[PDB]
Image 1 (tube, each protein chain N blue to C red):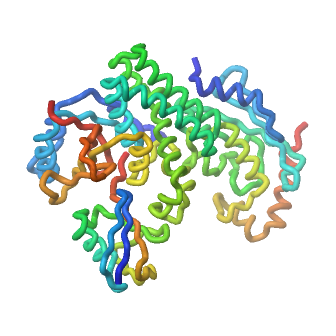
Image 2: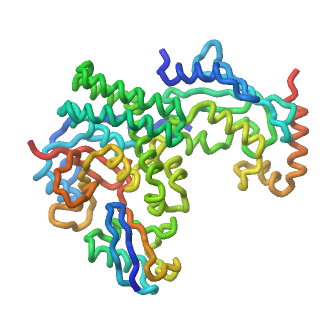
Image 3: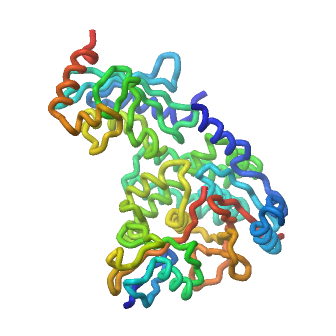
Length: 248
Length: 149
Length: 76
């Protein structure tokens, strides 16, 4: 059956990581006749957000969205990239010590490190980075590093996160089944782990059809007493994540 | 020109001695491997050798290897076409796993054939209801089909 | 009786409930404190997802038991 050939071909008619597009492109998916509730939320969001970056919906969208967000900060901040390149080496050692399979998990790390170093030295331009994030072989190899640290963060902190897993699964079963494999949607627990593991700070604009608090549903992860601005903002629509950008 | 993953895994597959498992790249196609797994001691498959075929698909390691038994075997996890019911070949595959993992897990499957539930089909049901007799049939098929030349 | 609801966000809250209470009513009481609406909430107790139609007594949830709250954020 060439059915999953056509399914995973609908997915592939869009790029992994689109170029920027005005936020009004999101509003144009909707209208007052058939999708009035979504149109309202999008139009509202467009007062704050000027642009959207569509991420392919292939099961990896959340990981790919965070990864794209992080790489964007690091193209604009040489210091932060230095810090991220080093603290990724701390992950390699963490992985191999938390008993992840050695040479395979090491090779994902090595590929990711080399990619960052090549940004740092200037070998890779901005253009070259987006091309790499759109080439399936390379982009997914890079994305695996992020699935791995998400899993590692949970295993590192297992007694703490164990009670938030349902279906009677242990943390290791959850990681093995829902975090480590590719094409697996991310849920809250995974999302919380990646953001903390990656040391980032995210606002999720939770765009659904429901009457909402002024400004729309949103979640800041982490949420703490501090009022630091989020460095990555995601658009969540039911079952899907894209990247969005405040105006100017 | 192969990706880095297949170059590295090929080198490991050639270097690593694994008891009862032999694996070779096809001379023409670098993604194609020929695998022989010895019937483990203390299983109905003892004395037999089982040929398996493994293919690394275009997106490997992001998708699972494809593995099939060529040697006919009476086992709850293997059907008439030699297709293999195994979690790490579909849903619990992750790219942190490797060919070695799959091969070792197929080997352990021969040693512990009874996986609590009937994966497929009439064979599995025969295994839980009358093990002694399923075990005997497996022994016979080993003699009939897995006994070399 | 009092129960606790622990969140991934780092917070624990307390609710006044009856064993008669449905999981729906419990979510509404969480909503009154947090703002998080019921259809955005998943509650877990003893690795088992709590079902909207059911009661606390159905899961033998006791005084000072802790429930775990996650948000509905599943995305590909």
